[PDB]
Length: 446
Ligand code: HEM
Image (cartoon, rainbow, N blue to C red; front, side, top):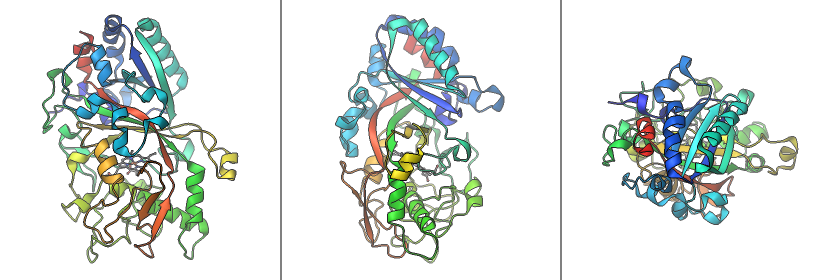
């Protein structure tokens, strides 16, 4: 069974602090680094057990993950069982129809050896922890890049930068989570390496870890808002209400969290707020042909592209359990400043903001990489539809900088096509392995 005392907390619980820092480092002296990894990092790594208890949240929650080159630097030559992780995200960029020439330069390579995730309710406490780490490790650790992130303010807390409530939908791990209505239920080994029904044999010290896909995804918020107004479907409501409908058609949920599949023509903010109801759907509706009906939710909507539910078979009534092996745990957090008055008034981004994307899975080829390449970026996914060309995911779908053709968004005519500029721009990232806590002061410090 699942040993949550040994699993790093961000994987299954999230840090649930107002502020986070992603501190990307190189290891310069493995002997000194190992000594301090065991003495200074391991004792303050937050576990799932610790973060699951309202009364044991630390002042600074800390997790740590290593890239392939970081494990090599530590003398760990084992095969962790993941070719994508071993090769690094830069080499995978073409799989997503993007180029590393657009990336943060530090990500366009394999010089990054790991990431420390620090989380606290204030940045001052994060900075103090960083200063301590740099003091005790000396030059054996070196900062190559960092990204600060924060929960958004006020009534946008928990929403991403486009304004949509985020963090609603996650896989439930059988035997660990109590499933919510409509939630997929998966074996622990989909997320945790070496856990139940992970088919890939792992090094013994790596049991209890997970692969972390980090993505710095810039969001063009004023441009997105203006696009919705400019393309809003005709109807009797206000222009902004119709623009909001188009945005909800693109995501698959209203900004409140209400799923369009259950409320297709107007928001239901009470539904969006209710975790017992807001995920209780499969995309099937009796009396409608699943292969052609886009009146409830477009086939191209973001959440339908990333968790297809009945589009990949299984139960037509909730819970649908299809494609459990393609599940990911998400712990992303927004970054950058809030949109300023001048940016909104000019419909133009002038500062970088977006999502610090964090996806956890036991197999990169089945999780993040698969969702991006085989589903979101695939104009013929989901399969078996009419028209067969679904188009790309309007939120994350990529085609080498081209405008994306996205079909089915307009309720009055499912054959109507839109050519949509990117509103999310990748600045790159890296693939890491978040080890079990025992490996931090154990194998990795040996
Ligand atoms: C800036 C980029 C992104 C934005 C703005 C975004 C936004 C959202 C929103 C608003 C939701 C609905 C809330 C929820 O169901 O929890 C969602 C769900 C989801 N997103 Fe994205 N997301 C982004 C990137 C990604 C990427 C890169 C992936 C994977 C390749 C991804 C995978 C998912 C999944 C799996 C779900 C849950 C689907 C379900 O279980 O029904 N997202 N996202």
